[PDB]
Image: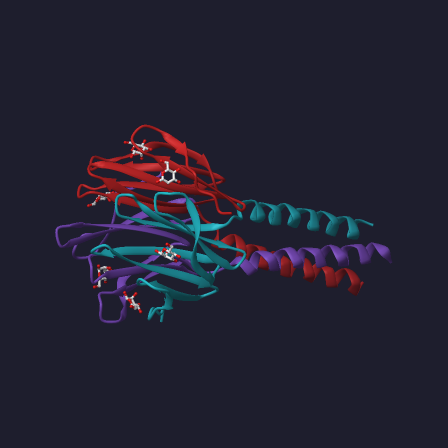
Length: 113
Length: 113
Length: 113
Ligand SMILES: OC[C@H]1O[C@@H](O)[C@@H](O)[C@@H](O)[C@@H]1O
Ligand SMILES: OC[C@H]1O[C@@H](O)[C@@H](O)[C@@H](O)[C@@H]1O
Ligand SMILES: OC[C@H]1O[C@@H](O)[C@@H](O)[C@@H](O)[C@@H]1O
Ligand SMILES: OC[C@H]1O[C@@H](O)[C@@H](O)[C@@H](O)[C@@H]1O
Ligand SMILES: OC[C@H]1O[C@@H](O)[C@@H](O)[C@@H](O)[C@@H]1O
Ligand SMILES: OC[C@H]1O[C@@H](O)[C@@H](O)[C@@H](O)[C@@H]1O
């Protein structure tokens, strides 16, 4: 019947659309750096978790940052030689700020409101 | 019939794929900062609109920036004490540059070409 | 029959969900800047390719950077007057670092591990 043949091309069209959406998919990164060496921190949202990779001039290694998020952005600044980093990790519509200030990642005051 | 049973598992498979796509979805953020206080600006693309949240050392508040976009990136620089911000808001394939230079957001010269 | 009418509303619901996913889609940008002029570089992931647009104070032009990627982030730093840029281009779960250090884009040591 042409009733079943119609829906068989309907699902075929939906497979073309879903495959186009899946084509664009990838991990999401954010990067910051400081000084002249330099130091570089690269944050990667992958499968709902954000991890950190670090460079201080002598090879790449995994940093202490490990939090949930499907999206990430980062900024940092120097107070003298001391580095301060702010990572904004988002899941759904909730965005949590994470703060490095010398020894450990803490939850920041940021809200979207 | 096994004709109807085939399409009933076809749509069931498409529900698994669409749910996987929706799982990764979230708001998209960009951040910049300047000075030593510091000042921080956080831009959030949510539901086709980009809004701005601000920190100058004494709590978070909503900034003047409000434009359309599903994606956002930002950079900024200091000319002395004066801050200049450039926000690149994208919808589809169109990317508009927005310029802060001391009093108001203006449309920048940027084009993708 | 109500067997065919059921699947005709099933596919209708999947069209609403796919259209919501396609609504959020856009090009993805990252930006960096340096100095006081300033110089600005804007990277755009579009249809699996990342291109670069440049500003050094006298109009926008297309830069040498051209690599594959569905996601992009960037950071840069000055060693004196010399600019160094690091672009992290991601496809699927693979993230390649690209390095500008004065004459040409080279593949960087970065790995996600
Ligand atoms: O030296 C490694 C450490 O560097 C700091 O700047 C932060 O990025 C930490 O998360 C990281 O573990
Ligand atoms: O020290 C913690 C505080 O640091 C500031 O720079 C901001 O990032 C605040 O949102 C944060 O709570
Ligand atoms: O002080 C608030 C103002 O700060 C400026 O740097 C910009 O971010 C404006 O959009 C904002 O309204
Ligand atoms: O002052 C306006 C101009 O400022 C420059 O720094 C660039 O961002 C231009 O694209 C913009 O049009
Ligand atoms: O002046 C143009 C050149 O500027 C450099 O800083 C890099 O961004 C190159 O990719 C670009 O071609
Ligand atoms: O000069 C090449 C090297 O430069 C460093 O700053 C890092 O970005 C390395 O990952 C890269 O391989």
